[PDB]
Image: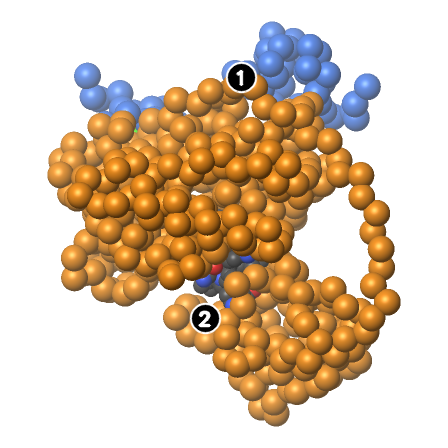
Amino acid sequence: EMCEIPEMDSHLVEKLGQHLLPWMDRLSLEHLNPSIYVGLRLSSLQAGTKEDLYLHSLKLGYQQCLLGCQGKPSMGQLALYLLALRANCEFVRGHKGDRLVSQLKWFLEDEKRAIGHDHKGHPHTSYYQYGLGILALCLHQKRVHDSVVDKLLYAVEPFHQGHHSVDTAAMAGLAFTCLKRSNFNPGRRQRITMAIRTVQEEILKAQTPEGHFGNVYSTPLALQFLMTSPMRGAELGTACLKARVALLASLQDGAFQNALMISQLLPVLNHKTYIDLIFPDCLAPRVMLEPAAETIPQTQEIISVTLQVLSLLPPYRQSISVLAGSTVEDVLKKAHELGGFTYETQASLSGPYLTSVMGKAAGEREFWQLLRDPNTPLLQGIADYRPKDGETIELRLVSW
Amino acid sequence: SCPPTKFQCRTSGLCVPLTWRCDRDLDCSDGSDEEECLACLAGELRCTLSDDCIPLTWRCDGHPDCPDSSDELGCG
Ligand code: CNC
Ligand SMILES: [Ca+2]
Ligand SMILES: [Ca+2]
Ligand SMILES: [Ca+2]
């Protein structure tokens, strides 16, 4: 059976795109987002001339910062910039292009070395970024050595060490699919074929009773991967229809606010995936997005949220009053204003990433986890999760 | 129409840096920017005309990782 997601309501799709639209005018390097560009080009929606300026800004920023900048882009982000080039039917080229390719190849080589011949060491970033890097190079018909591919293969193959999310497995599966379709790494062809099936099975076995694969925000990338190949013996069609039901409910309940998440979902709703960047169709008709004319009524209600940090001595626990509809980040700002609380964030393609709390920065294989009561990890970041009145938000330094 | 120290791609109307002016790369759609004007680690190999080291596995992989492209030149 095949993974098919029947077209959703055009109105519903349009309002998703309108969430992306304001970002088209935010061209500062801290806000530039190659994933947004890619998601839009693969969608049924377009931003017209704004897109061309956006790509131009991407090319200026990425090439000047990495070859010649305030907080220049990461290698993982460089990989997504490569996807953005494919989305405009370009191959990375010229002397500047060649150098960018080799920088991404160095990233993979360093992660391979960090992982080790034994496969105990972690990558310095994630296996998600490792897969993303292989995919990005493959889309531009750039080859990586079998030894590089081997680390991704071992990570998903039987008796692998560690546990990977649905997102990570899906990204790996996409990388494997590009290798297979391009007939790259022929000395790993059978293992690559087997790994794709392995990822299929693990993703199907991660489907919740609601219908999501892992969770609501893993479902888009999971669907992208599942759409790329048949899955004989399995009921892929049924699983994907159940996911659509789950996806539809989540959409109608306002689950998708984050621009990166929308950019990963929009291709799915247009029956496209990142694998369509092998043979891109850049001139396919797309509906022009217009700004949602829309009032912005302020709330009149005050809510109180308890913010707590038990990972530090002495511990922090305070009730914070904010306007209803405020984000966790607003709560953090208010806590800082009241005195006795500090924090730090850094920019990412998903928005502000919490890196430090009350002077304590997360170290290697550590992060500040966001939770609500009771002991429940948030599915959104500080700038997207909007706590309800009486909620308790916890920041917890954890190791993974 | 655009700031000094940045060349403007004439057909596009877009503006790009002088470093990119006459640098063999087509950065403008109108190509106006061009005509108008140490030890190596084990398992690595040195690029013939420079200081650079690359992994041995980058030899003959279809992409010039060396400035002088010497890592693909040998292959034929
Ligand atoms: C790896 C990973 C993943 N994560 Co995290 C998970 N699990 N994440 C990060 C890890 C980063 C560290 C590392 N060494 O890689 C990890 C485990 C620590 C992290 C943290 C969690 N993650 C979380 C979520 C919910 C997000 N994460 C994802 C991006 C989920 C991702 C899956 C996905 N579908 O995208 C994910 C698989 C891949 C991200 C990536 O590398 N993209 C490629 C990269 C090139 O882009 P980038 O923007 O430069 O990457 C940076 C950011 O993604 C930042 N970051 C990671 N997660 C988030 C989440 C938010 C909300 C923000 C603003 C930034 C981040 O870390 C990366 C830098 O290394 C997201 C889809 C995952 C999911 N399916 O649930 C989701 C995000 C949902 C959404 N509505 O936006 C947490 C909030 C969980 C929690 N309750 O604490 C938390 C972030 C808290 C904080 N301190 O701000
Ligand atoms: Ca969201
Ligand atoms: Ca040039
Ligand atoms: Ca080479």
Secondary element at image label 1? loop
Q: Percent from the top left, x then y, of residue A222?
A: 38, 47
The secondary structure type at the circle numbered 2 is strand
Q: Furthest-bottom residue in view?
A: A314
Marks 2 and 1, how far apart at CA: 44 Å
Nearest the camera: A233 or A353? A233
x then y, percent, for residue A209: 38, 61
Q: Specify few, some or many for label 2: CA neighbours under 10 Å numbering under 14, 14-19, or 20 or more.
A: few
Q: Is residue B19 above or below residue A306?
A: above
- Picture colour for chain A: orange
Chain assignment, label 1: A
Give chain B's shade. blue
> Residue, x 73% and y 16% (percent of image)?
B13
Vertically, is B13 above or below A339? Answer: above
Residue annotated with mark 1: A283
Q: Which residue is mark 2?
A: A366
Q: Are there few (<14), some (14-19), or many (20+) residues within 10 Å of tag 1?
A: few
Total labels: the figure holds 2
Q: Considering depth in this image, is A317 or B35 the residue closer to the camera?
A: A317
- The amino acid beneath tag 1 is Leu
Q: Position of residue A362 (x, y in %)?
A: 51, 71
- Quarter of the rendering occupied by the N terminus of chain A: top left
